[PDB]
Image: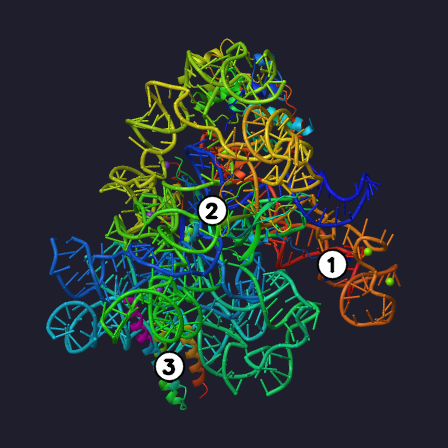
Amino acid sequence: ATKIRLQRHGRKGYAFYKIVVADSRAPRDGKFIERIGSYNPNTNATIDLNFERALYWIGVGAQPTDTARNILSREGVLMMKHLLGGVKKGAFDQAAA
Amino acid sequence: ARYTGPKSKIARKFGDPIFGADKVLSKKNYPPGQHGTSEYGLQLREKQKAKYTYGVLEKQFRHLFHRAQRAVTGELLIQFLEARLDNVVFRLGIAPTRSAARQLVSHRHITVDGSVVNIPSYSVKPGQVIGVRERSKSLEVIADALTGFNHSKYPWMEWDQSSLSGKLLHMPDRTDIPENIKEQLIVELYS
Amino acid sequence: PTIQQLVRKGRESFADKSKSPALNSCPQRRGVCVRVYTTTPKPNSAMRKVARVRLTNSKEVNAYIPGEGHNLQEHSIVLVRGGRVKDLPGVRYHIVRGTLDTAGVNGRTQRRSKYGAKRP
Amino acid sequence: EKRIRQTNARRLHNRYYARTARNAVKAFRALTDRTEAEKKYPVLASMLDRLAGKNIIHKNKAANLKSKLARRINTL
RNA sequence: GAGAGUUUGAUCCUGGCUCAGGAUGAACGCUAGCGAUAGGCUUAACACAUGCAAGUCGAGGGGCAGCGGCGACCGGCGCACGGGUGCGUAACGCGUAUGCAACUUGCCUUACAGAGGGGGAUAACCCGCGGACUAAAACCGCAUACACUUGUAUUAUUGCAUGAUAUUACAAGGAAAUAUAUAGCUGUAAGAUAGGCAUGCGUCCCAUUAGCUUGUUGGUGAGGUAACGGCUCACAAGGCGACGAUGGGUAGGGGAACUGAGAGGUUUAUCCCCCACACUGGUACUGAGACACGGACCAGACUCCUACGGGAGGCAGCAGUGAGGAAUAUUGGUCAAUGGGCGAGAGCCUGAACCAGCCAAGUCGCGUGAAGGAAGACAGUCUAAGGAUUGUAAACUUCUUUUAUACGGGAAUAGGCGAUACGAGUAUUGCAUUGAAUGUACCGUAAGAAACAGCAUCGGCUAACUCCUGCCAGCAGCGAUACGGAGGAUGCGAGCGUUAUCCGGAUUUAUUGGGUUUAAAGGGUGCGUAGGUUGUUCGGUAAGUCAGCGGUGGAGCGCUCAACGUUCAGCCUGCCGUUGAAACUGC
Ligand SMILES: [K+]
Ligand SMILES: [K+]
Ligand SMILES: [K+]
Ligand SMILES: [Mg+2]
Ligand SMILES: [Mg+2]
Ligand SMILES: [Mg+2]
């Protein structure tokens, strides 16, 4: 299936991951459909993320891995519950906390 | 590697007092050897003079040269050579000679911006602080070179004896650096 | 030629031959000393020591023996490298000293690495 | 051994129904009477559709066979 | 964006050759301290033995002989991926750009409908390769679905020819899985993903390779396929070729990488995309998907074992060993991280991957000490003077680094409380192979740490002794300011040289950018086919040409510094689509 995962694109002893959308059958650092961000666990962890594209792929049904799911839980990408029109029409703001 | 050999032989070969003052600069001053020139000879003499006076080997010197070419090329190569941790420490007077400055930097005695840097080739950008280690401010050898001498003849160092630090205002122009090196010869040789 | 002549025919570029064809694009080869003999130079008048060697690449060539004093003999396994001698027609290869059967030159104190002599 | 046994059993199972369906279409292809063709069509179409939804053959193959037989019986 | 030598007694040209430079998954000789980050059978799709590499589900079923969970069997999913190799293949194989109104697509997401009723074997077990009873989310009917398929229509709308999309109908036919709220099951549609087919242009030499083809070219019909089609099967005759058909030889192809101011070129070592393959051929089968990489059957080598009745392996997965060779490493650790497979989850597995070990080892960085100390002893060249030489010897400090000790990070992030009743947002819990590994700190010490090449010209660097053949060389050549040693000198420096391969100077294939009287080079001379070129002028067109619009394909930050990682400004200037212009070429 289509997945959201991290490819190790760095140096020995310095792991830098690229957040991409790719088929499950593709190799880990090989082919991908779209690049949606970056990830660095060495700092105290800087995350770059395309919010619109990540929302689009999680809406069309790309299954994220565990670490990519945590990265999407951060930066508020899993707000599809709030954006599903759950008997409301306004948009809440939880990013400030 | 490092030269770690005889210095008076190089001093008598080049004539100029690159390492400092010595009695052999005035007594028996001639190129060394029991037996003792083309423009190649003079260019090689100039390049080796720069290398010996700044403690740089050939590959590092070539890297410095083409870095200066990428970013007058001979004019800024000299300031690139001057902007070095050992050279800046030596010019601040905290160490007697350039070899002493190199050893002091290589050992855990010199900090840059509060962090100890022990690479004696680290390029020092303008507006940076180079200072003695706070754990090595009370060495017998560390004080006689700075205190007492107090040359302060360079209008690009700020000393601030009350903190034992030092600052580089800006890269000095090619006329204010007291080095007898014709950069045109070196850039012609490497061109 | 005219532009149309070049369009019809074009330009042809030859291939430069290799100066050591018996090595088969290898730095060194291994052989056996088929014969050990002496040759005369083509205004020198010396006695140059050469060996006819059959290399493992199915080829037989002549290899000069540099230095003074060779312990080699017939049917000896030797290492053969490129390099020719100007005043000797024929030979175009050298024998590496200090490798396999060939021994280093005794009593050498200068240019030691070119003749396989250790530090004394 | 398990894979070999499963493949042999499934091959025999598929061969049974595929050969039965092929024989059914072969027998239907020699019919002449319109009423006989009309009363023999639905069971053959049911068998073909069961095969197609049962993955012995393909849905497009069953559709092609059904279309061919219907167009044949539409012209006596 | 450059040159040097070399034909002569001495010139100026022409022309080859040789050096000088840069780069290797290179090898060899001499000599070797450390750290970081790369790379490691280039020779043969060579042989061997051992072990591992693809399993998982007791929330599917019969059993428990084993204390809860599970050996084994039936069943579901996966093993077509990850990984390895470059044999074969001048081909819609690949690159670039499109089309499918001729296509298929498990797992995933969303929407709409449904899960009602039954019956056979059979594995294991039992009893001796045979006999009997067994269960299903295994297997197969029946009921239902007009959201699907098939056939006949009506109303349309609209295309690119064959036509396509929707409605409104009749007819026939086609499913399921339940288990302990969760996990789910079936049909249909849309999306996403992955494949398939067909196209325009580009894609190595040989004419001491000139005709090739007989389902070959087209039409009708039928069959077959996911699908069009000579894909296959039962009239006309064609089609393709000097813009190179056909035949032969050699290559996997691109981005990269290296290298040239540019023109470009070389080569696929690591890395990524596509293709082909799994000892050699043939056939398939199972599957959503197969050249089936740890699946069959048969036919061929070859190799191994039996106990002569019979059976096994393919080492182009990861590691030992042997051989070939100039030459390339451990029968290592862990699933902690990333990625996969299965599972409701916990979790299990993973020679992918993370790591470590070995290897002058490609690149980068550091050390082998820092400041003073007069002209010891021992070497040379001249009985004194000069070179070694501030060099040693002591006397004063420092520890990068080595050693002994301690602290030791980071890579590790993932019960209630709204409530839409489920998502989702918040606490807690263990979790490191690397690993005394970075780093930090403490004693007592310069203590443990420098080679190699060449010094007569080109070129940086000269005395004396040998030899006067032995020798040396890239050239002028010497056989010595050229051979061998001793003293000094000059390069580079944990490296220095030798060999092999590839580029530039080379304009030594010259479109940019060469020539043909005498240096190589005008056909013996004409006529003429294909082809190339086209006086002047008036209008059309828009093929070349030009322009616009779309689609596609240096500055920071972190490594203590640097190599190196990483981000944005910055080219896309190649291809395609769509609008305009008309001076020149073409018509
Ligand atoms: K962190
Ligand atoms: K399947
Ligand atoms: K893992
Ligand atoms: Mg180095
Ligand atoms: Mg002539
Ligand atoms: Mg004539």
Q: The residue tagged with tag 3: helix, strand or loop? A: helix
User: Dot 2, crowdedness within 10 Å: few (<14), some or many (≥20)?
Assistant: few
Number of residues whose C-alpha sits closer than 10 Å to that of mark 1, classed few (under 14), some (14–19) or many (20 or more): few
Determine the CA span between mark 2 and mark 1. Answer: 56 Å
Left or right relative to E54: residue E457:
right
Q: Name the secondary structure under disc 1.
A: helix
Q: Is residue B82 visible?
A: no
Q: Residue at x 53, y 40 (%)?
A: C115
Name the residue nearer the viewer: E224 or B68: B68
Q: CA distance from mark 3 to mark 1?
A: 67 Å
Element under label 2? loop
Left/right placement of residue E486 relative to residue E223 reads right
Looking at the rendering, which quadrant does residue E236 occupy?
bottom right
Q: Residues within 10 Å of mark 3 (few under 14, many from 20)?
A: few
Q: What's the magenta region?
A: D1-14
Judge whether residue B47 can be spotted in this image: yes
**Residue that carries the numbered disc 3 in the rendered image:** D22
* Marks 3 and 1 in Cβ contact (< 8 Å): no
Residue B3 in the image: x percent, y percent? 52, 25
Q: Are marks 3 and 1 on the same chain?
A: no
Q: Is residue C13 above or below residue B102?
A: below
Residue behind mark 2: C100
Residue E556 % position (x, y): 52, 33
Q: Which residue is mark 1?
A: C6
- Quadrant (top left/top right/bottom left/bottom right) for the C terminus of chain A: top left
Q: Amino acid at mark 1?
A: Leu
Q: Nearer the viewer, mark 3 or mark 1?
A: 1
